[PDB]
Image (cartoon, rainbow, N blue to C red; front, side):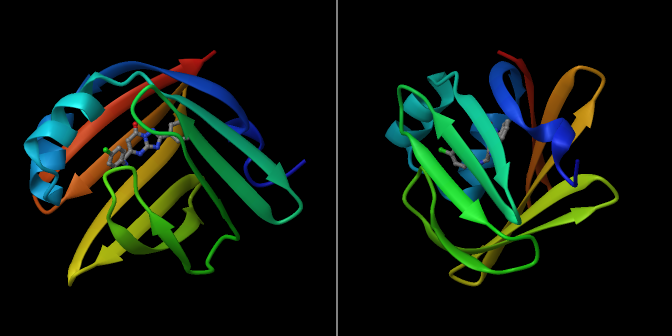
Length: 134
Ligand SMILES: O=c1cc(CNc2ccc(Cl)cc2)[nH]c2nc(-c3ccccc3)nn12
């Protein structure tokens, strides 16, 4: 048993707050915001050795990242940003930092009760997305 055991599984989006405003702050254009905001993604987390895989499957866009904690990787986000990402575990929270064009956003993922809570921060704007087991 290891580092991310309580994250592993298939999760379904059950609530969202402020996501449109977060996407605006990131620089996502109107049409992409509208379609991405409608999505109800399933997020699938798995671990094999030191490699963590996070897949996001939705009607908008299927994405997949695999990574080792602390080790930078290149990521193409669902809104088509080309970013440099680093994911670490900080006090039991997965902290995912994306850097591009001189900008930075942080996505935190944590277990709280039977939920997986995702907090997306770009400058002063936070969006909270709550997932439950599928
Ligand atoms: O709902 C979101 C939103 C973001 C923020 N990235 C993002 C940026 C641009 C767009 Cl257009 C869409 C998404 N990251 C994120 N990770 C997970 C998640 C949930 C459960 C298990 C594993 C991962 N959900 N979630």
